[PDB]
Image: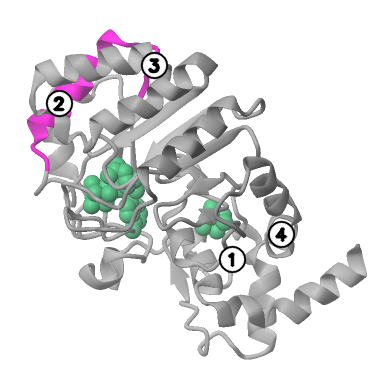
Amino acid sequence: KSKENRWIL
Amino acid sequence: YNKTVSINLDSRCNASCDHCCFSSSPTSTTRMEKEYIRELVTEFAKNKTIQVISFTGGEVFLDYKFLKELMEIIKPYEKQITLISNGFWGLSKKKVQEYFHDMNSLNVIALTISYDEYHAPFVKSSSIKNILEHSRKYPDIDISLNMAVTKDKMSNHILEELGDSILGVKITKFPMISVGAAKTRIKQENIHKFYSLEDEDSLHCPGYDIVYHHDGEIYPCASPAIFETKITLREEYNQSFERTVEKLNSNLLLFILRKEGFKWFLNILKENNKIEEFDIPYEFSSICGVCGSLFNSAEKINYFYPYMEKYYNENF
Ligand SMILES: Nc1ncnc2c1ncn2[C@@H]1O[C@H](CSCC[C@H](N)C(=O)O)[C@@H](O)[C@H]1O
Ligand code: SF4
Ligand code: SF4
């Protein structure tokens, strides 16, 4: 978690 | 958007977190077939522009034999891999040693572990501690801890009980997106509100990241919110990554979103008095909460069509 577009990664 | 790709391996999980955006559980049955996933991974490994392949779920370490097989398919192509896990496998230090040895040998550049009050009923704190401590032997694997929180469950005691195992580990606490189990199992007043329908200048999507999801669809990002939208990039069963990238770059809705921000869509709903009709909430924990409310039905997406057609005619 940092930017929302990679939230579940 | 063609240097990274993600695959959601399964909705099955050993945990049943009350916030889970996928309502994952041991009895979840949504997933792409194993042979189909092997073909996707082989294609992504062979692809010349993809640099990173990320795996998520569900719990990807649940069927470790399959995860290791996929990482071995990628190995000759030297792509970087990222993994995210609830760390249930941390219970045994011998298992932790085996998995870190494999991750190191298979170009895993990042491992994210999720632990908080929602995951705590399913995974013991000692399991998380074993993973975090062993990670010190592998400084080339970027290790992080994700903590999903609500006002009533801020994970303060969780972090204290991890003790010195969290030293040197990047920790991020984040609020909930109201999707999946979070919609029905968490009181909406316990979800933090950081944005409102008024701060339209800060309503911008951070970017796209292609995800081949466990429902067999393809999504433009890996936010929990997107998976309940009807924004998909899949047009056929055997679709190449070149085609997925081309579709993402030519999607008019996503182009307008990138260029104009959420205010473009919100102003149309406001001018047409559709905010209540489309159940757009007034406050949100994240910009993705605005995204999910605008596009979580075919009716909502199709409502914008004549406006997007007019935008295309005036600007293209
Ligand atoms: N509704 C929701 N809102 C915000 N974060 C959520 C969410 N549902 C799941 N997450 C977070 O999304 C991340 C990936 S969930 C899948 C990977 C793994 N089972 C895990 O738990 O890490 C986790 O950090 C999880 O806490
Ligand atoms: S948040 Fe992760 S560990 Fe919890 S139920 Fe969902 S997929 Fe499983
Ligand atoms: S704003 Fe929408 S498209 Fe952008 S990361 Fe969030 S859910 Fe995905």
CB under 8 Å between callouts 1 and 4?
no
Query: What's under tag 3, amino acid-wise?
Result: Leu
Q: Are marks 3 and 2 in contact (CB under 8 Å)?
A: no
Q: For numbered disc 3, what is the local secondary structure?
A: loop
User: What percent of the width, then of the height, locates residue B64?
Assistant: 24, 31
Kind of residue at disc 2: Lys
For the point 53% across and 68% down, which residue is it? B230
Q: CA distance from mark 1 to mark 4?
A: 26 Å
Badge 3: residue crowd in 10 Å (few <14, some 14–19, many ≥20): many
Q: Is residue B18 placed above or below B81 in the rendered structure?
A: below
- Amino acid marked by disc 1: Asp
With B8 as the anchor, is B15 left or right in this view?
A: left
**In whole angstroms, how far apart are the C-alphas of marks 3 and 2?**
23 Å
| Mark closest to the chain's N terminus, 3 or 2 | 3
Label 4 crowd (10 A; few <14 / some 14-19 / many >=20): some
Question: For mark 3, what is the residue?
Answer: B106
What residue is disc 2 on? B129
